[PDB]
Image 1 (cartoon, chains in turn orange, cyan):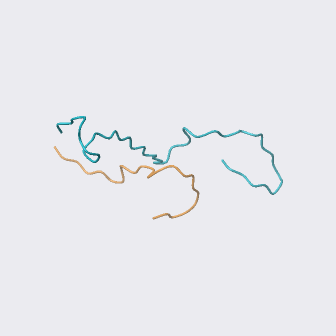
Image 2 (cartoon, chains in turn blue, cyan):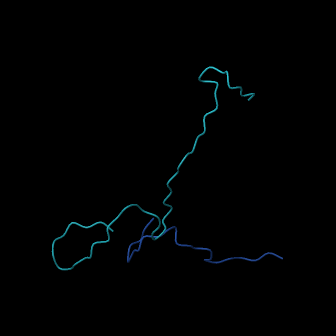
Image 3 (tube, chains in turn orange, blue):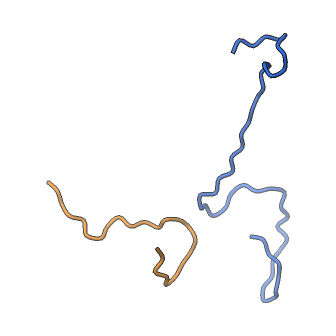
Amino acid sequence: AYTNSFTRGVYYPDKVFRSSVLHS
Amino acid sequence: YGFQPTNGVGYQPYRVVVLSFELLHAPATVCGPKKSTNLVKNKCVNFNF
């Protein structure tokens, strides 16, 4: 079988805190 | 290498050590002869963390 993720597999690219900031 | 004691320099064996300091993004690790010295707060200060 195969299935569809929707919005899955997002990890914090590294340390360094951060707040409201649409960071790219 | 067939090393032999009667070899001119530049053919004698040299031992090598390569130190590589890495800092992926850890929170803290090894250091040097620091001092710790206490801290403060509310005063314009020159700091090193």
